[PDB]
Amino acid sequence: SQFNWFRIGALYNTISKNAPITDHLMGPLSIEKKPLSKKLGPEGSINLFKFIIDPNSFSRSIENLFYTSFLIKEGKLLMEHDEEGLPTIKIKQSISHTDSRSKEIERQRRRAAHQNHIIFQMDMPTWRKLIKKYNITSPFLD
Amino acid sequence: KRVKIAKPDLSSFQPGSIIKIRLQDF
Amino acid sequence: DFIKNGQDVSKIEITLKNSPNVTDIEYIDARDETIKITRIITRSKRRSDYLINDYQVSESVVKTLVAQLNIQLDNLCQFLSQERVEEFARLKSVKLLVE
Image (tube, rainbow over all chains, first blue to last red):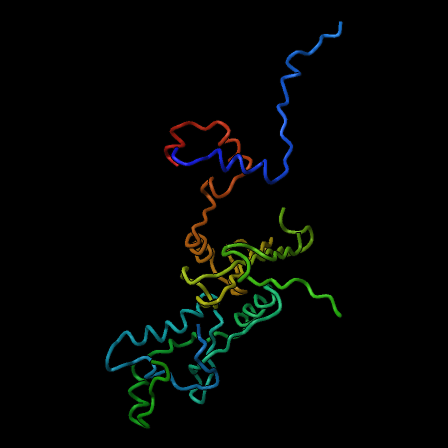
């Protein structure tokens, strides 16, 4: 309450805006009542026998299983038989089908096919046995 | 040209929202 | 009721925006912006099997995803049904304090 709030108000509504102003008396007062795997590439495959063992750590096998763990939930993982007659580790492409039931049809197709659980893939004796022949084994993922 | 339905771009939609819903055999 | 009379499987698909703040996801990257969740009901099979970007999972994964999206089904605030409407109709101050 220091500035002229009326002089500006007097300039407005009078000089400009040409606004009609009327008292409009109280006429109605008096109203008459009127009465995840982007980097990986699929085609490579290698034996898994030292893919699991690492001289550094025993848990290296678990991270190898962790590669399967991402695929365990839907079960798309399937490794193919090489000359030894046992599944061989390889990388998997991203796969997609038309509708949500089409891939479901795909998964129960793989379950219907023969499953590779006759012998647990990681076993002690053969890994040493292959080391003695060619000393190759080796992991492709680390 | 051939009629194209509006692109269900999820970036434009706010996070957690739903653009297209498919109902099959109900 | 959901399953079409005669049809074996009834399918619902729902797509949501994805952000790198939720874990335990299948086939979907953090930078990806799409989460596709599919539920199928069939007469022959009695199990809880859902689909994440068209990949079969147990109900636990989708449940923990729903938990990690800060959205809840049992809680009456996020989801309101006829029974929940009736429960809110006669609501005491103690329930307000509890919520």
